[PDB]
Amino acid sequence: SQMDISNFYIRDYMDFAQNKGIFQAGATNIEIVKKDGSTLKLPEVPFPDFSPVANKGSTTSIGGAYSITATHNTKNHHSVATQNWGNSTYKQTDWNTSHPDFAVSRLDKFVVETRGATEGADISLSKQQALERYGVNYKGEKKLIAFRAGSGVVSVKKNGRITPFNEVSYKPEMLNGSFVHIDDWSGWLILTNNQFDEFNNIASQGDAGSALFVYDNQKKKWVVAGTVWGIYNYANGKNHAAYSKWNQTTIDNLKNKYSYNVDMSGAQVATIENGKLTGTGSDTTDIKNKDLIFTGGGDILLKSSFDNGAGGLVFNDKKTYRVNGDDFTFKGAGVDTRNGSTVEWNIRYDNKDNLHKIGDGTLDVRKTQNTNLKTGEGLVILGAEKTFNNIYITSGDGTVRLNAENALSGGEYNGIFFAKNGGTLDLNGYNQSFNKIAATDSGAVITNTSTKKSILSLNNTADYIYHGNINGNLDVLQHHETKKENRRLILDGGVDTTNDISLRNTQLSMQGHATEHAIYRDGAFSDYVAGMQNTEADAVKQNGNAYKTNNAVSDLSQPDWETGTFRFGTLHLENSDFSVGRNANVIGDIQASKSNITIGDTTAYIDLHAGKNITGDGFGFRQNIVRGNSQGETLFTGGITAEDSTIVIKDKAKALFSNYVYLLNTKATIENGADVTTQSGMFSTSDISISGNLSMTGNPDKDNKFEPSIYLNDASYLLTDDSARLVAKNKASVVGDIHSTKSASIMFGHDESDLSQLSDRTSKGLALGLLGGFDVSYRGSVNAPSASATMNNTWWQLTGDSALKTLKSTNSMVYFTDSANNKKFHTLTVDELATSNSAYAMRTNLSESDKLEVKKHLSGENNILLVDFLQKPTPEKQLNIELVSAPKDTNENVFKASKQTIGFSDVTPVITTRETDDKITWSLTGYNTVASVDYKAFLNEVN
């Protein structure tokens, strides 16, 4: 544990050993960011799972009740005589040692926290064979590189200067490691160079016994090469850690010595009474301190209580067994169900001791135990009411299935505690109510594999973060009778169902998870955490990253978060607050009533005990929520139906409304930097305020085309910022007035070059109906005198007096028309109009008309003026109705009279051009007679 912190952080070496930060088990292409900003690529291997390494580092699990270490630590060493993994304590019963310094320990219980490093390296391989079998690519070469972790006395080295932390040895929190080069493989001891390159961490006193791991090509599996014997220092600063090789036979002899085979092939019933095993092919009068290894299937009968000492119960074939015995009890190392064995457990485990379950098989518990389970592997069926008082699930490999009504216990957690990497609780058709789920990370899964639906109620009484997952066939419910402050439910793990979540009088946040890192000391305080912090105050000062050395598992200001994917059918909101914070990917529909929805909440939540929530012996839960500003990108995708609600989409948030949005008396706001795309239609009764980006498009089908979509606002689109952007394109029919005090942008239609096609789903009748042959229909007035509008391939049904700063119309029709109760003529007022290949269709009753007024600049070629004659003109009256008004220098050919009729008139307009001293104008000064509408067809006249 002598760490060169010249170009790396102390926490990097800790994260490495502890599978925290970037060093997740199995991860490839890991890059350590140096203090100088550049990157160090790890060797090309799936990163090792270091869970076999004991809390103190000097001992390592090799599976079951066995661990390996260094003989010269001694039988009595505090890290050998007692050995810990997670919240569990294990006592050494004895050990077997082989020269030079290799020790294998027999423990008193089956270790549930880890499968262990079950296999060793083949030390009989030659140099070259070993390089081929165990070599890994590093800086473009195959090298015999090994990985390891330990917690010998800590010191740090910066550019030569060593700073020791003499008290700091065997500190679980300080577990640290490195990848190292094996300089000597075939020699008497394996010799590793821990400073062969850059990530340099030399072994120090207390690292003795810690394991060396190498990666097997063929087995695709990390295996143990040896245990730390000692350390050599040579002239000119060279250094090796020396390793006592894995000795398979020392292991096998100890294992066999602590095993006793019981052959029940055909031999009816195994009976155990006061330490005597009868009725089998392997009868004896003890049988104590030995794993009983059962084969052949069948019944085990206790005629007395059975304390097997350090020995456990092992089942070693894919057969079924039954353990019966009055009200007698078992005590020992636990139950190891191997090779798919099924054990129907119909006795009680000792009431003052924890049952340890490992093995890939099944423990089917048929009666109430009145004691605790610790499980790490395979299946446990809870077949009785209150099967266990408490359950501790660790490592990720274990599953607990409810198979009875009322199967869990009471209290805040229902007696379920998910420790490191958790495991799966299968509700299996039964409903459960938790006040809180005591889970420490995202490895905790609550699910339901039954075809019968189950309901998971969460009733947390104060603020609380659930780190786990909710999967499978379950609905989620959080209902309170009154809405109170200070009991928010925060999900920062995940949800993955096709079912519903129901919220009533409550507050819910969905959120990503701040990645957990190693810390120096768990708890407050002379002070080594302060000293270590001061060693890197220079680096922190330079890189502005105080979170990195603050002795906190995570921090609101850190950049590394894990996305929370929340997939569900419908989220039902009744008088509730729903928030999506940073780094979420929410995928589902929302139905909201009297509710507040916030997408892009700047408040995020972190748990200062994340990853270390499970306390004591495994059956307590701690959590310390910190909250504050922490912005980051986030996503919602789906539909929303909202009544009497408010919706806010905030900065960095992207909302893809891929289903219908229905806003009934709901206040909707899209803020600066927020991005909303709606593609499956909308209805709104109230104003939508847009300071960011609202894009309204048709529905993209499977074949690169668009089904028309309708955007119906009975109120107004309010553009509330200079930076606002309202976009409609790709087969969208929009209805509703636009108002803006600001210099926002409006963009209707696809880009001139970039055409889009109709879905084969859509009949041509419907298409003409909603779009008039154009890409976009817009119906409403626009009063945004400072705003810019761009319209291409657009049908503007202009239904009221309108005002823009600048307007550009290419291949569009501005169609002046009426509504329910207008029936008045309208005026389009613009500072600058650039118009080409477009049509303007004005109505007239032969004295007034719709009118276009361009105040400052009118440019563009090839536009027609259509006139809807609402009354049949006669040859008597002198017509002289101003249709368009523009500045003097405008070219008269910008507009021409159409030779087509529009409306119910058989009459074509005659338009004449005039120059007053300040404005040129187009006036209707005559007419000509000709003896679901496709309005795009009109534009043929102007190509």
Image: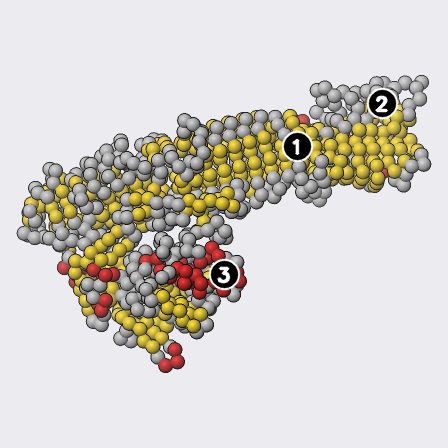
Q: Amino acid at mark 2?
A: Glu
Q: Amino acid at mark 3?
A: Val
Quarter of the picture containing the C terminus is top right
Q: What residue would you read off at disc 1?
A: 717
Q: Earlier in the sequence, mark 3 or mark 2?
A: 3
Residue 206, position in %: x, y? Answer: 29, 66
Residue 540's tag is: 3
Q: Earlier in the sequence, mark 3 or mark 1?
A: 3
**Is 146 placed above or below 943 here?**
below
Q: How many marks?
A: 3
| Residue 331 visible from this viewpoint | yes
**Is 5 placed above or below 505 here?**
below
Residue at position x 44%, y 70% from top? 158
Residue at position x 35%, y 40% from top? 437
Residue at position x 28%, y 35% from top? 410
Quarter of the picture containing the N terminus is bottom left
